[PDB]
Amino acid sequence: GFAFFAFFAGGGGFALFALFA
Image 1 (cartoon, rainbow, N blue to C red):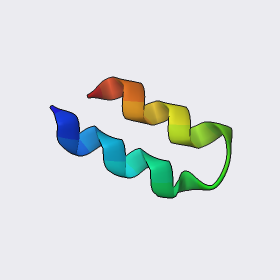
Image 2: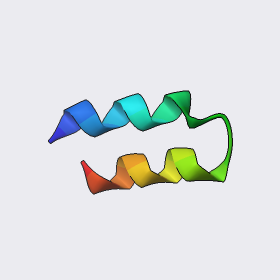
Image 3: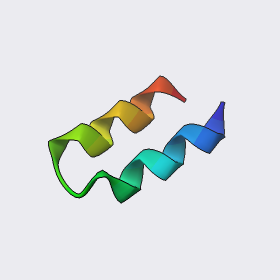
Image 4: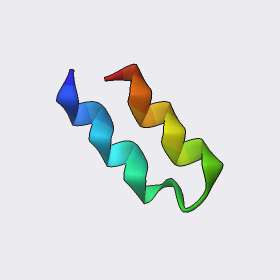
């Protein structure tokens, strides 16, 4: 689900975990 966009708070390549959305 699009809540995964909160991954953008990762502050680096781990923000790509937002693709889990």
